[PDB]
Image (cartoon, rainbow, N blue to C red; front, side):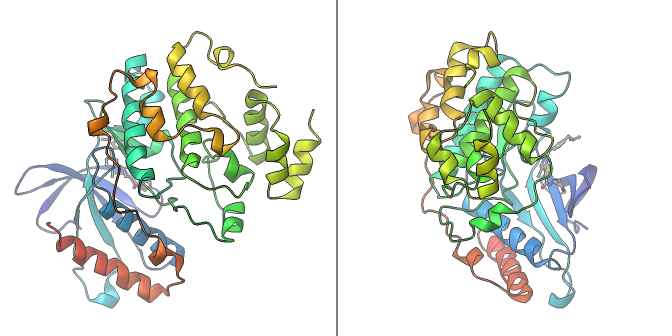
Length: 342
Ligand SMILES: CN(C)Cc1cccc(Nc2ncc(Cl)c(-c3csc(C(=O)NN4CCOCC4)c3)n2)c1
């Protein structure tokens, strides 16, 4: 599995099309995570997502974004190469376990976690990359309370051709809980503000240590969102993609203050929260401006919240590539990685 240069420790996850084990580099002793992606070239959409992920990760160099530390070279003939091994930063837990466990989660924990999330997000949005699928299970953390953003299978970027119908109908299992309203309602406004909606959801979830908008189904999700944010505005309703969603929403009979949603919460925390959770994307705060909000004064540092240049190009992802060309690009990605340190 891991060749001679690593040693396996324990399995961290096995479901889905990947195994995640913790390991140690034999020569250095550094601990890492090894992700096996089996049958990585069978399902064109899977291989596309994988190539997407490898490129996004190789592009980012940022302490709050998981880094690729090694990619195992193909140990079998090209045509026989079917399992991809990606070595990543080993983290100790994820924000979900923290929120839904027996461990401390003080307002200072919440403040520092939010700070690192928004710092990663500032660097990431400056590269024209939208994560689109943020959630506590996607935020990795260690003992010191350091946070790293991961995954990225769902990241897309700023251009949205009439591939908005693609967003119309896609699979989201338990993942509509943080899905931005513009995606729930296909408002055809797909920018980095998407992520900010989720951040708000995550923020409140740290505050009360319970999910904010836990819809049991699509319609229930919309109903929950509305019971708090109040009836959406005329313009929003008119921008909804599917006439049927519009009709249901119009066939419905006010916003509840956030001090009432989270009675007794840090004033500044709820200030930021309210700046995040709004229907109109344009009305949300940017990651950059959030980092300057009073709630984060403890950690704000303008010389240590860098943008990322150059921006990230999704052209490779936009073109329809055969299975073969996708596999070719992934192998080229591995070799390129080994061409930029090891
Ligand atoms: C030590 N342990 C008992 C506690 C624990 C619990 C959860 C996480 C971690 N740390 C960690 N460090 C590095 C990485 Cl990279 C990951 C990781 C999580 S999820 C994932 C992925 O890519 N996909 N997931 C979806 C389905 O397939 C595989 C998983 C990669 N986690 C530690």
